[PDB]
Structures are given as structure tokens and as C-alpha cells.
Image: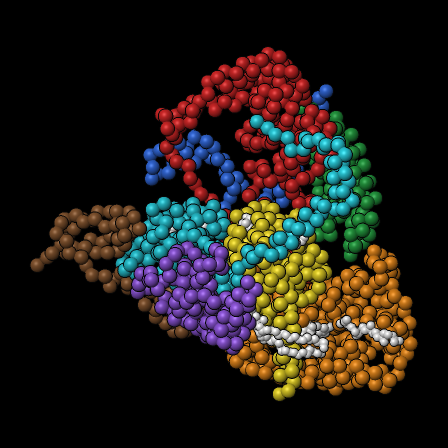
Chain colours: A green, B brown, C yellow, D cyan, E purple, F blue, G orange, H red
Amino acid sequence: GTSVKPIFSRDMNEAKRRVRELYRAWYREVPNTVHLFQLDISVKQGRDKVREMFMKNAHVTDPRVVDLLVIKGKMELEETINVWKQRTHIMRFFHETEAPRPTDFLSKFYVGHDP
Amino acid sequence: GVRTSPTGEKVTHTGQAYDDGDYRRVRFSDRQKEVNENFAIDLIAEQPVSEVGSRVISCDGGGGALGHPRVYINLDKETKTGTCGYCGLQFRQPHH
Amino acid sequence: SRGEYVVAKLDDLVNWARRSSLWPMTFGLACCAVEMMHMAAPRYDMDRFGVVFRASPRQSDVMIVAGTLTNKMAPALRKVYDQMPEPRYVVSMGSCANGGGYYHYSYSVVRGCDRIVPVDIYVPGCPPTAEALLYGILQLQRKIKREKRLRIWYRR
Amino acid sequence: TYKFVNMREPSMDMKSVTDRAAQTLLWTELVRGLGMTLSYLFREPATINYPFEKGPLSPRFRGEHALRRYPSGEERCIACKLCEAVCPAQAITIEAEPRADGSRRTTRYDIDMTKCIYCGFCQEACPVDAIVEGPNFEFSTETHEELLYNKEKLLNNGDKWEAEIAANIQADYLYR
Amino acid sequence: ELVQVLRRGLQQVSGHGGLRGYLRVLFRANDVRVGTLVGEDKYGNKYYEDNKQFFGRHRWVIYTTEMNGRDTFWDVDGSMVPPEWHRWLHCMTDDPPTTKPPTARKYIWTNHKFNVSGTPQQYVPYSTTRKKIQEWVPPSTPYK
Amino acid sequence: QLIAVDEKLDITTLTGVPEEHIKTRKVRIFVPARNNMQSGVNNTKKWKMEFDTRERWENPLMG
Amino acid sequence: LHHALIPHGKGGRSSVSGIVATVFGATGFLGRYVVNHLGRMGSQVIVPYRCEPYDTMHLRPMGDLGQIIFMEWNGKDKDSIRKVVEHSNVVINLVGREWETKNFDFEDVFVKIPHAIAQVSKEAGVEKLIHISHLNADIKSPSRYLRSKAVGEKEVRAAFPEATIIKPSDIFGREDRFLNYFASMRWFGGVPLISLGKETVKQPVYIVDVSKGIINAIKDPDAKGKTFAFVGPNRYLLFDLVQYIFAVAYRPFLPYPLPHFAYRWVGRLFEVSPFEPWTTRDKVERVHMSDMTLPHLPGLEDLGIQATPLELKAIEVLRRHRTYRWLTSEMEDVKPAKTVNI
Amino acid sequence: TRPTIRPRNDVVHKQLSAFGQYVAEILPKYVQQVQVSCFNELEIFIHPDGVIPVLTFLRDHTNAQFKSLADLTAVDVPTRQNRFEIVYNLLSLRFNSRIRVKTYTDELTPIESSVTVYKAANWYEREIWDMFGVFFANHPDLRRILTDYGFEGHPFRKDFPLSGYVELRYDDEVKRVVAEPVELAQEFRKFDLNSPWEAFPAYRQPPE
Ligand SMILES: CCCCCCCCCCCCCCCCC[C@@H](O)O[C@H](CO[C@H](O)CCCCCCCCCCCCCCC)COP(=O)(O)OCC[N+](C)(C)C
Ligand SMILES: NC(=O)C1=CN([C@@H]2O[C@H](COP(=O)(O)OP(=O)(O)OC[C@H]3O[C@@H](n4cnc5c(N)ncnc54)[C@H](OP(=O)(O)O)[C@@H]3O)[C@@H](O)[C@H]2O)C=CC1
Ligand SMILES: COC1=C(OC)C(=O)C(CC=C(C)C)=C(C)C1=O
Ligand code: SF4
Ligand code: SF4
Ligand code: SF4
Ligand SMILES: [Zn+2]
């Protein structure tokens, strides 16, 4: 039993429905975000970034964790829609000023001690 | 007691001086390297040794509560002088 | 040469006009702005030097960063710095704006406003006294007295 | 015990009613405010002529830091690191080793002045009055790096301001 | 009593050595009050007091026209005041250094320096410690 | 009512920690050894968790 | 490798990169990006300047504390160069002026100064030198600018044999004199083009690509004596490029043909400006000259850089030139131009 | 014992103990523990399900009348299975008294919003959510209050680092403020201050 209480959803199906609703809202919002914030990206890039952000935690199997993730996504969408966010906040999702970090063993061995 | 290095850089009391190879000397170009002129080791070496007529002497650094904590120094070793661990002043007993 | 003399005199005149009429933004962040107000108070009367607060960035010449700059605030400070018409000057006032100060190791504080904007003068203290801020302002005036814009243009 | 600030009732006789009507129609209280501003116009202002005149300070004033010496010229600091331990901003960095003559002395004594809150805890913690906050407060710089003091800078400040620092200490050490 | 004020102004003009000194002190310091001379620096600064003024205006300094290397006829700042007169001028004591001289020490600066920021004499920070790790020096002779 | 989850607890996606400081870190769970300079034992009563030591280098300015 | 110059950290603002670079001409269009890329990873940057220090202020937030040092230099004084390169292991030369001043001509800025810099750097012990040239540098070019470029690169190669020479083609960016220059022409009314721009081919390159290529050439041990050509991915006819520029800015495009002599006469008139000229005869010559094809030289792709097309970065330069009515238009609205490729 | 030691008021201590017994008797369904400290402060430990009934009773009862919410905050104790401790500080003007109500929760269990009981609670709950990540059910408008827009993590948690994971700076190439992983010129220096000799025998724990 494990005697746990929910936040919103009882099982993973309701959680998936909430995830789909949040994804629909973000997908609808992306073009307006590109227009209002005067972004130099395309709408396709924004929608790809939204999809990548959703896929970053596609491995979650706890409905409570999914519920909290959806709540946080709604918070971020509310920040974006009301323009509380600025252009810098929107563009932090893309990491434009960070040099790529190599992932193979040899490059890591060459640069430093970090594993 | 500042002495110059082969590159002309002044040597600090701690002894730090940039090497010829080192690139950090560029920070002093069109500017100066701050060095204190009063080497405390040479100044404390100049003080005369006090002669007292007891085996134990007390030092507080002078000025009462304006000096250092008061400590007591043993003066039994005839071939040496007692040194204050705070001030550096030296004391001894009259020999010869 | 005649041209060198003319440009030197014109540079002197323009520099005098700029430094004698210094209008800072009405802008403060934290504790240090109280000392800024005390510098505007009768005892020191910064207005007697020609220094007048103006609210709009388009009508301001100097920005005094007086208080802690947090991560939430940095884009706004940068934005009102960008909207100042040139020439413009930045004065960093207090430990917090200088290098972070008491909050240097916090997760939400910019470690010095000079990561966000270029700074002309740094005023030390937590907070600096109104007299110290007056000294820094007069130092900025003396720095403006030293620029050579027309002479350098003529030497090109 | 309490009092009311706005719990009064105006008089309703003809005399006071006409008084209030004359106040409304002839602007008496506004004239009074104008009179107060006029009175202030003819007073001597409180402004001083800086930098030729300075604001008053006290011997306890906390300014730019300095390192002090004994009358013989030997340094007072003995690298106990109490000031480093107590500093609420972690603005002091110290390294030490035995000197060539065996003395306990520092090799690094750095104060980040853009980290310092100028609380004066370091000079309270010092047991030999080696580190003090001196009376100077006019030391603004044009670059950030000029406010990162090392040991040479602090010793130079001590040698530069000792004549005033010693007199200031003489005037307050009986309160400490 | 208006004539008294006007005469006070004329004696303010006369007490600065005439019109030339009056205009010099009006354009250098923006003030033409006449005080009593307390003393003079070795750098040329002069110090005055007038106890009839209110607290804060009862002491002042007329800065010198030439300090160590720069012309200070117009460019003056509070950092040109030496420490003893600094203590007197900020009202941290009642006794001027003339009547109450400071203690003489061999290490105290004999020449005061003002704020040197922005000049070639500006302070540049550096690490004062020596090298931590010493590298191995390979031999200078061949091996075969 | 209750929902009766049957998974394993995993809050990593909610803590905001970057991916690098989750997968490449190794924490140590231990009771600290007594400081051999003192006889007191009051610092060896609890368990401690600390992360693996990473690189430290000298600052070009101020060292 | 001199222990103090061994890289440390994760390559951020407070790291050590092992690079000590002197960047001549760091107060220009390319210099700001080069200094920013060097300061991002914790390099010690030395900035020689001749201008008023007010004009070097924007370079200050580019480095950590102590990592950017400003020093005065004179282009015609050898000891200034010696003083500003005494301690560097890399020297990057970005000095150059589009127009000829009374005190400095094209030969002064593209031959004499680069040669003096190269000779002093070789004498001082600098091990890496980066020199910037033009893709169209030709000894018999109709432009004195490009002839001086060719002479200067020859002399620099003579003085510093192991130098790396980079030849870009019409760099475009926010502060560029390329895209911005075309935008400026709208105020007059029409856009005067020689032969209507139908016989000119351009291969512009993004500024960030050039800066990254320079940074990579510093870190590449194989690029010691190499010579690179930095060009964009597409080639455009001048007419199509200007039409696209005007379309992105949403301005009416009115191209009319102007004969070469008439244009030259117009260029001469503008040149008399004591300030920065709006255009010059040399600028008109270089604008209406096709970009050379040099397939025997290594390019951006040989330093790990994928060149950025103009169609992805034009909006960030041309949104400033729009009216309020078109300010919010997005990037994928203006239908990219036709490229004459192969 | 006279000059340097703080005086203790016995009469107040007796009154608070009696009122704690009173409250525990009236609400046995939720009260798990009642405590009175030696410096005269009363604490009530409740089950999370009793947040609303207990607060409502303490606000509306004639013998209670704690009509003001002085403070609401959280404390993080990682060694506990329920990580977070929720503390309500209430003040009674009618009887000139103060009371403290405590409960507990973990990362995934919401707590009922107390906004209906107290208007003042709306901001406090937002701060608890922002700093600790505790979710409050039925909040009128729950969102970040103190942290920067888009900030990730909850900084008041013991596990969160003091300096965070990212910093801000202005970048000239993109012409905006950018966020990057924290790098420090001088690392914060950790001090080990605790004495190896025990200070307070009255608080000694059994040796397990
Ligand atoms: C025709 C309409 C258009 C042009 C309008 C021009 C208006 C007339 C110009 C007004 C001239 C007055 C300015 C000079 C007053 C400065 C006084 C003196 O103090 O200046 C000193 C020296 O001044 C400068 O070195 C030079 C100033 C003047 C430069 C040359 C004059 C050029 C006049 C040419 C006019 C033509 C205009 C162009 C026409 C197109 C520096 O001292 P300062 O730092 O302040 O004070 C320190 C503060 N203390 C005293 C309290 C300690
Ligand atoms: N921009 C382009 O599209 C192309 C550029 N290049 C080359 O790139 C280099 C720079 O490009 P860009 O930055 O756009 O040119 P800029 O004119 O924008 O930068 C010029 C730099 O050179 C310096 N400079 C010019 N003349 C002198 C001088 N006489 N003495 C000292 N310093 C001087 C300027 O300093 P100050 O600010 O004091 O003048 C400035 O820092 C040039 O060599 C140019 O030929 C190559 C191909 C195309
Ligand atoms: C009267 O002119 C002044 C202001 O303009 C209204 C200010 O805002 C300020 C700043 C204080 C307010 C509350 C912003 C000062 C000090 C001032 O003198
Ligand atoms: S520097 Fe000190 S006084 Fe100024 S805002 Fe920061 S904490 Fe307040
Ligand atoms: S005054 Fe306070 S903050 Fe400054 S160095 Fe001393 S102890 Fe540290
Ligand atoms: S300055 Fe004083 S407290 Fe600090 S290390 Fe030296 S002796 Fe100890
Ligand atoms: Zn002693």
C-alpha cells in the first residue's frame, strides 16, 4: 500500500493527461513569445526547445513527481505569458555563451582532472 | 632593507620577486610595485640587549595595556639571550 | 600650431561644462541610498556643486549604484544604463556594489556591478559616509577634467 | 495609557462658523505655510564648505585599515589569525611561517576592501593592537583592483597614518 | 545696522590682503570669511578657526597651490591634509598639532602623499608569497 | 483517499541540481575520526556526508 | 611551459587559459569580439589603445579582476610596441582603417604598422602571431586598400615567418560597415548600384565565426605558418543581397544603375569630410568587386567552425533599421534570397 | 545567581501549561504533543491533517482568540523522514499571549493552505514554497516570491549550496545578461569550530 496521498492525479494516466494539456498550452504560446519578446530564433526552434525540455524528464514514473513537474511548468508558462520574464530569461534556455563541454574520455583527460 | 633583483624589481620583506620568465610582471608596466621600505627584521635587530639582575624578567611590549600580553622570560642559559615571543626584544644577565 | 590650441581650448570648455553640470539618476538600491540622500541633505548640499537628481534616464548623466545588486535586479540596472544618452558615467558606491560585500557568497547576488556595467569610480565603505561619496563625485569631476576627445580626434 | 489624535469637534456658533468661512475663502492656513517658508529663507543655512570644511568625527570612527608597529619598528602582528577567524565577511586572508630569525610573522596579509563591511571586529579581536581601522575615509579608486590590499599596502598605510592612529587609540583605550 | 554689515564686508575685503587676495580666495574656495591662523603645514596648507561660527564651519583649511608634484591651484581634495592636521580638522581633538605635536617615530612617513589613484604611482596588487611546488630540473647532459 | 504508489523515491528532477553534479559525484557517509590533538570525543557522535574533492587552483590576481 | 602558464579550472571567467595575448586594434568592430572570447575563458588580455579611454570602457566587463590591462601605445613608436608585447605569448593584429586620415594613409596602417608589430614581436620572443588580411588582397587591385593589404601581408610574412594570416570577406554584424552601410542608403531615396549590382558576387561571413576562428587558430598547433580564408556558406549577387537587406528591414527598395565614373565622383565628394566619411572612392571600388575564390587555402571548417548563414543572423542587425510598424516581425517571414552557388 | 542570570516567571509557566492541557483535551484527534519551554513559550505539535481545524479553533474560540498570524515559516532537518517542519506563530491580543503550532511534511506531500483562516498567510506560504519546495493545496495564487524568474532549486534546503549553481554577467556578443555555472576567484573557506568537549550536560543524549 505504502499509504501515500496524491497532489492532483491518482495514477499515471491522469498525470499524462495533465502533461499533454501543459504541452498544448506551451506549444500554442511559443509564437506569441517569439513575437512579444522580439527573439531572433524561429518558432520551430522554440517548439523544439519546449519538446526537449519536456523530454528531459520523460523517465519519471512517480505520479506525484509528474504532478509537481506540471505545476512548475504551469508556473513558468504564467511567467512567460504575463511578461514577468525578460528576454534574458527566455534565452537562458539555449545556453548561447557556454562553450561546448566534450564528453569522450580523451578530451576530458586532456583538459583537466574532472571525470 | 630592499635589494634589487636582476630584472630591477624590488624584493619585498617576505622575499617575493617575479622571475624573468613570469608574465605577471606586465601588471607593473606604466605603474609601480608597492614595497614597504622598513624591514622589521633589520629594525628589531638594531635594538640593544637589556641587562637585568634576575633569572626571570617580564615583558609587556611597553605602554601597559597598549602593548602585548604580559609574558615572563627565563634567562638561565648563559650563552644565549631571552627573546620576547611577541615584541622581539632581548634580555640577558650580566656575564664576564 | 593653431589647430592644436583651438582644439585644446574647446576640449577644456566642453569638459568644464560637462563636469559642472552632472545630473545623476534618481536610483538607489539599499542602505547606501540613505547616505546618498544625506549627501543631498542641507549639510552637504550636492546641488551647490551643480549635481541634481533627475528621474528619467534620458535626462541623466551619472548612475550611482548604491546598494546590493541581485540577480533578479541586474537586467533592470543594465536596461536603465543602456537608456542613458552618452556621455555617461557610472559610480560604484559601497561594498555590495563594489564586489558583493557581506553577500559576496550568496546564490542571488552579483559580485560587483562592474560585471554588468563599466565603472568609473569605486567608493569604499559599508556604507561610505556622505562626505566620502562627495569625495568620489569630485574625483569623477577631476577625471572628466582630464579627458582629451577633441585633441585625440585632431591627432587622428 | 493612550490618547486620541483626531477626535475633536468644531464649534457651531456664528463666530467660529464665519471664522472657518473666512479660512476657506481667504486661504489663511496657506498663508501660514508660506510664512514658515519665508521664515526659513532668512535663516543661516546648515551647509559646510567641503572640502575646505569637514564633518565632525570621533576617535572611535572606523576608516581605512592599517597595520601597526612597536616603537622599535618591529611589527605587532604575530599571525594568530583571530581577525581572520572573526571577520564576518571573510575578507582577510593570512599565511605565515617562521621568519629567518625565528619570529612568528606573516607572509601574506590581504584584506579585500570590496568584501569588508567595516564592522571593526578585527581590531577588537586583535590581542596586540596590530590591525586597526584608521581615520581615513577618502580613498576612492578608479579601478576595482586598487581596493584589494596586500601586506605591503597595509604596512604603508600604518606608517602613513600612525601619528593620528596612536593619538586616536590613546583617546579611547580606557573605554575598551 | 545695515552700514555695520557693509563695513564688515569691506573689512573682509581688506583682511584678505586687498582685492587680489580677496578674489583669489573667492575663486579658489568660494568663501571670503576671515579667520585666525592656527598654523601652517610644510606642504603649504594653512589652517584657520573662528569660534563664532556654528559647529562645522568654525574650522577650515586653505589648501596649498603646489603639493608633491601637481599644480593644485584649482584641483584640491581632502586627501591633501596630513594626518595630524587631519585629526585637528575633523574635530576628533581640540588641540592643534602646533600646541600638541604627535609622537616622533623612525618609521612614520616624513612626506605625506595624497590619493594617487589614476596616476602611475597607483597601487597594483600582487601575491606576496613564494612558490609552493618546485619542479624537477632534468639533467643537462646526454644519457647515451 | 490514497493512491498507493509502488515506485522508488526519486526527487532529482525537482531539486534543480545540474546533471553533472548528480551522476559524477560520490558522497562519503562516515563518522568523523577524533582529532588526535585532543582527548574530547564530542565530535564523533553524528554521521557526516560530504562530496568528493575537486580541483582548486591559484588565482592569477592575489594568489 | 612556465608553470604560471599551465591551464587550470573549467574554462570560465575565473579560470586560467594559459594565453597572454596582446590585441592591437581591440577598440574596433572585431576587437570587442576577440577580447570577449579571450576573456570568457580566463585569458590575460593586453589592450593597447590610442583613443580616449572613455572609448575603451565597454571592454572592461569582458574579463575577471586583473585579466584585462590597458596600456597606451603609438603606431609610429617602436618602444610602445616593445612595452606592450614584452610579456605576451600571442599577438593579434587587428589594426586598420577603412578611410585614409591626414596622418595615416593605407600604407601606414596596412604595411608600416603591421611590419613594425611583427618585427618587434619576433624580437621580443612572442611565439604566436595572428595577422588579419583581406580575401581580395591583390597586388594589382584597383583599390589601394587591397594593394596595401597584399604588401603588408608579404612584409609580415617576411618579418615573422611562423605567423598565421587570416583573410576574411565582408564581415557582417551588429556594428558592421557592411549590412549597416546598405541600410544607410535608404534616406536618400534610391540605391545607386554600378551595373545594377548584377555583375558582383559577395560571400559575407559572420563576425562570431571570425572571432571563434581566430581563437581556434591560437589553440591549434598545426596553424603556425598557415594562411586561412574565412568566407560564408553562400555566394550572393549584389542586387539580390541588397534586395534581401531591404526586405528584412521592410524598407522600399529603389535600385537604379549609376555609371562607374559618376559613382566615383560621388565618392570623392563624401571623402572631404573631416569626420568618418559616409563613403569613399575606395569603398565604392571594394563594394562593386567580386569576392575571390581561393579553394587552395584552408577555411573555417578546418578549425572546427560551421559558418553561420546570413539568413539566420540578418534580423539581429537589421531590426534596428525598421519602423515601429514592422519592429515585431519574426525572422522566418522575409523569404531568403537566391544564392549563385556552383 | 542574582545579577547575571535571567529571572524565571513561575506564574506564566503555570498558565501556559494549563492552556496547553486545555487545547490538547479539546482536540485529541490532531494533537500529538504539548510543550512549554523554560523561558515561557508554549508549543503544540499536531498531525498535518489538523492544520485547518486547529488554527480555526485557536482563532475563533472565545477562550483562545489568537486573531493574528505573527509568522509562518519552515525548518529543514534532512535526518528526518519528513524533511520539513512548518511553524505557525500566533499572538492573542485579548489575552496578551502567544502560541506556536508545529507540523511536518516531506517533499511530495502537500499541506493545506491556511489562507481561509488567515489573510496574512498568503505571502508566507508563497515564501515557503519558493525557499523549501513545500506545496500548499488550494492556494489562491502560488508562485515564486523571492527568487529570480526561472530560478531552479530551493535555496533554503540544507543540501543546496551556499553560492548556488549559476551566476550572472553581461555578455557583449549577445548584448544581454547571461547565466553561467558559478566559478569563484576565492572559494568560501569552511571552518570547523565545534569543540570536542561537551558544553551542556542537561541535553546529553543516551549512547544508543
Ligand atoms: C555664442 C553662443 C554659443 C557658445 C556659448 C559659450 C558660453 C561662454 C563660455 C563660458 C566660459 C566660462 C567657463 C570657465 C569657468 C571656469 C572657472 C575656473 O575655475 O576653471 C578652471 C580652469 O577652467 C578650465 O581649465 C578652462 C575653462 C574654459 C576653457 C577656455 C574658454 C573657451 C571660450 C570660447 C567660447 C566659444 C564657444 C564656441 C562657439 C562656437 C578650473 O577650475 P574648476 O575645476 O572649475 O573649480 C574647482 C572647484 N573649486 C574651485 C571649488 C576647488
Ligand atoms: N570589417 C571587415 O569587414 C573586414 C575587416 N578586416 C580587417 O579587420 C581589421 C579590423 O576590422 P574592424 O575592426 O572592422 O576595423 P575597425 O576600424 O572597426 O577597428 C579598427 C581598429 O584599428 C585601430 N586603428 C586604426 N588606425 C590606427 C592607427 N593609426 N594607430 C592605432 N590604432 C589604429 C582602431 O583603433 P581607434 O579606435 O583608436 O581607431 C580600431 O581599434 C582591419 O585590419 C580590417 O582590415 C578584413 C576583412 C574585412
Ligand atoms: C527633492 O529632490 C529630490 C528628489 O526628487 C523628488 C528625490 O527623489 C530624492 C531621493 C529620495 C526619494 C525618496 C527617492 C532626493 C534625496 C531629493 O533631494
Ligand atoms: S554596502 Fe553596506 S550599507 Fe551599502 S547597501 Fe551594502 S550592506 Fe547596505
Ligand atoms: S572591519 Fe569587519 S568586515 Fe572589515 S576586515 Fe575587519 S572584521 Fe572583516
Ligand atoms: S592582525 Fe592581530 S588578530 Fe590578525 S593575525 Fe595579526 S596579531 Fe592576530
Ligand atoms: Zn615583549
Q: Quadrant of the N terminus of chain H?
A: top left
Toward which corner of the image does residue G159 lie, by quadrant?
bottom right
Image quarter where ligand 2 lies: bottom right
Q: Taking G253 as reference, is B14 left or right?
A: left
In this view, F60 is above or below A58? below
Q: Residue at x 91, y 76 (%)?
A: G256
Q: Taking A55 as reference, is D165 left or right?
A: left
**Nearer the observer, G145 or C99:** C99
Can residue A99 be seen here? The reply is no
Q: Residue at x 66, y 45 (%)?
A: H148
The location of residue A54, given as percent across then percent down, is: 74, 42
Toward which corner of the image does residue A76 lie, by quadrant?
top right
Q: Residue at x 61, y 53 (%)?
A: D40
Q: Quadrant of the C terminus of chain H?
A: top left
In this view, D125 is above or below G40? above
Toward which corner of the image does residue H21 lie, by quadrant?
top right
**Nearer the observer, E30 or G4:** E30
Q: Taking H188 as reference, is C82 left or right?
A: right
Residue reaching furthest bottom?
A: C1
Q: Residue at x 68, y 27 (%)?
A: H118
Residue reaching furthest left?
A: B96
Task: Say how many tags the image has.
Answer: 0
The location of residue D12, given as percent across then percent down, is: 75, 31
Q: Taking E71 as reference, is H199 left or right?
A: left
**Nearer the observer, C133 or B3:** C133
The location of residue G249, given as percent across then percent down, is: 84, 64
**Nearer the observer, G331 or G6:** G331
Can residue H140 be seen here? The reply is yes
The location of residue E93, given as percent across then percent down, is: 39, 56
